[PDB]
Length: 130
Length: 50
Image 1: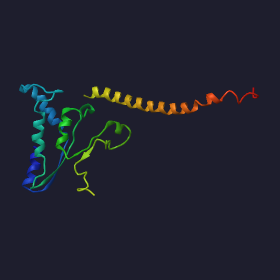
Image 2: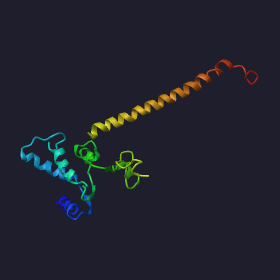
Image 3: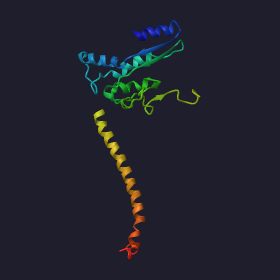
Image 4: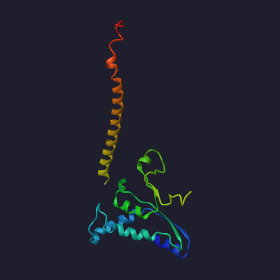
């Protein structure tokens, strides 16, 4: 629903819009809850088999086209601090800038608890930045 | 899975520990190999000191 509102502002109004989402994981979690009652065999860990396709359709809609631009900031919950989990991992390929927070950093009094060795950015290239 | 990787991280630490400790052995062995010479040249300076 919110993405549809942003798309209208992007296309019809031709404006540069911001889109904040918190939390995008719950979209996957909710579909997993209903997946069992829809007669679908659970996949690994216990998510729905359609985890990758459903998230991809939503993510591809969140993009900047020739008409307008959408700057999207999405918060991803890494269950039990396990970044190997299917949901957090599936969301890494659909992003231009990943900010990975670590509990150990926060416990040391460092805020924001960013682990720079695990973060990445697409524009970290000399051609784009100075 | 995190639980499995918890052991893997734990075993990862022990591996580096072995390497560093082995490096310590290399250092001491060199010092002992060069300090082994005194064994030849001792037991004669302290004669009238007795």
